[PDB]
Image (cartoon, rainbow over all chains, first blue to last red):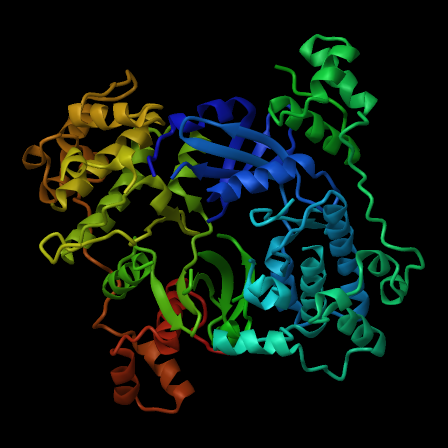
Length: 315
Length: 318
């Protein structure tokens, strides 16, 4: 729509665009003040899905959730500045590998479980967990995306039987489907005819390949209980015996990224730059309006974590 | 439907790689080893697609992104396409701020080639804009997105900044010439001739037809822009006069060669020979099957073998 280049003007204040990385257009970009790379979602206003995703992401902050840095609304456009995830979809990685070893699966699955536990702890349900919605960042860490359908009906193969007719329990079902696909490279319930796939899900029966360990088979049946009330709880999952093989500590699901605690180095650089003192800056930062100040703080925090200088660009 | 059975027939001929773009995954064609882009459509999730497909089956040209292979399954449509690593013309303009007149002409002669050929096959693209132009590895332009293209002279039934004033009221190939005018201006200025925050204002600027002329524009450039950006369609320069127009031929001294260098009728003997060896046929039999152009794996394999040869690499299948 439109084709206007003036629509980009306020954005170009803060970011330097680079090439499209996704065709809801997604461009790679550099945040000018920090030099950090980000992915920018460009929407031309021609959904309540976006408003749902945006509002969820304002309240969620976690090492396995793809981070919202900046929301820029223009007369004609909505811009979402998001964490940049060069590693691609978990889905791509699954196809490319045929199927994952139990050790490989466990590494990634502990991360999916980290993210989803945190989501539930903030009173949300994703309702659309599937490998297309999981991305690898530069460090090969998984990032949960796509909060359009979240609550305070995804894709069918991943949808719990309870959910189809008529919350956190369905996410556990979906993670169950995820775990099987990771270790098998194909779905537990699948068919060309969508009507047939529906009945399979409802019976709840599925093939179990020779290469799955008994441990895996047990976890799978605990997550894929067609009775929602029989599904394993998030609590028991966090330290489940399969989950802890090779690790010996439960999944650390608690967020490492606070809304309350500010980092002093970053506040310092922001104060100096905007010509303020700390209390003024800290108050402004803690309003989290997800304006340009939000982005610069989080990208500076992200810059520090990388071991780069805590420095904003001289302008 | 998140079903993976959908990929079964595809993974026979192609090995998928990461999404680069209705999703787009990069892929390798197994027999040839050539890189391709596979556009993935979920059927439960437009007739725009059927339109692009029937157009691309009939259009074949060095500046049109080539359709190699169409694969349809119960839930999905696959489209195998020429791979364009160089990106959108739009992004390259932004990265350069604006193009010199010489650079513009280099790029613009290719756009003219593509669109002239399109019109010559009885079509109008109807959505020319720099997002729909891609660079390949040789930094050559490839025209894409035939979702909106139509037969002007045919049976009945884009983005605003690029739309001719006539399209705003309620016709022909002449609206493409207008879009090519917008394109040329953007190439040389780095901003639109008609643009505004308010869309109603934008309709009106376009229909009035008046626009800024920056000082860095040459009289020649101004002259051509004036010929393409006629709000009255009958006054607009014709494709014929564009092809050999003086600005167009500055530095070249030959008109734009728009005629296709990629044939439906002439088959390449090496490629056919290699395909004969592989499918256990003789020449006349093999050639008969290739000429049916079904855009099955055979069409894909012939065209990618033809491309492998053009690249000057060995004509060899795995």
